[PDB]
Amino acid sequence: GHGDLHEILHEAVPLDANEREILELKEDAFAQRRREIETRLRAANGKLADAIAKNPAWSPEVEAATQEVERAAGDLQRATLVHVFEMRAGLKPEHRPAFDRVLIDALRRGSQ
Amino acid sequence: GHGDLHEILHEAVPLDANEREILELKEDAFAQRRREIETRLRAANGKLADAIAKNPAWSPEVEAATQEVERAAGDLQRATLVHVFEMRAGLKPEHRPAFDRVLIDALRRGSQ
Ligand SMILES: [Cl-]
Ligand SMILES: [Cl-]
Ligand SMILES: [Cl-]
Ligand SMILES: [Cl-]
Ligand SMILES: [Co+2]
Ligand SMILES: [Co+2]
Ligand SMILES: [K+]
Ligand SMILES: [K+]
Image 1 (spheres, rainbow over the protein chains, first blue to last red):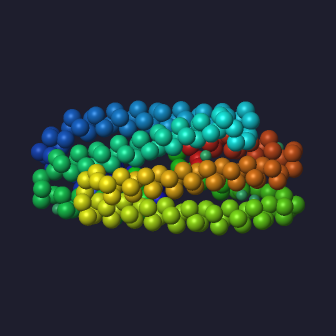
Image 2: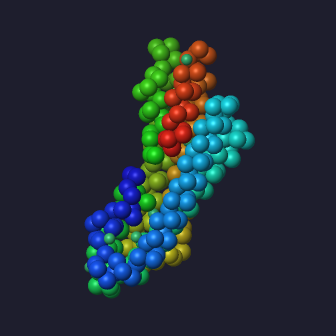
Image 3: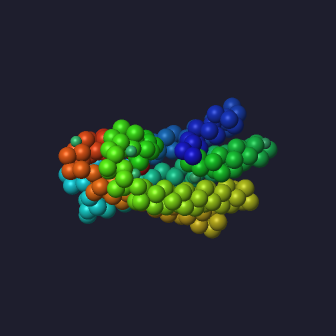
């Protein structure tokens, strides 16, 4: 699948009042990081489209654009999962098992 | 976005009767290849979920599962685009510009 793992967690197992206060800095830093990597992904998609518009074949331009797309997609996947673990660190310990249930099930479905 | 590039092309710019005959072998070979890589992707998602169920932290198990997911996703992206170029080769030349319009626009939106 193509689930939004971060959104799934904040909606299904929302932070409590104190957890939200504790996590606010890291949540903002993540929002900014997600936006930056998504800007890079959109730009890489544009480069791949441009390459194929110019010459619709495998090509050095296509090879480079494909790699750039892959790299940005991987950076987003990894950054998201690191932030998911940041969230888990900021939870009261007793809230972690419910969080994990949602996380495990969503990962199995391909959410990222 | 998360568009299904292959499906977008076959639906918006379907093959004509003769093109469909010419392409049938390569279309079948691609269907089988897509299914194989998707099996690997689902299995990699399962390994990542398992890893995090066991120990919800970055870990050698998470590192390996994440890489396996990335590798299968890239293999699928590349195989799809190679087959898109197979399709273009099997088109009557006069049909290629319409195909390219759909392809370029869909790539720009992130379809893969
Ligand atoms: Cl929340
Ligand atoms: Cl809990
Ligand atoms: Cl078709
Ligand atoms: Cl045309
Ligand atoms: Co968060
Ligand atoms: Co096809
Ligand atoms: K993930
Ligand atoms: K692509």
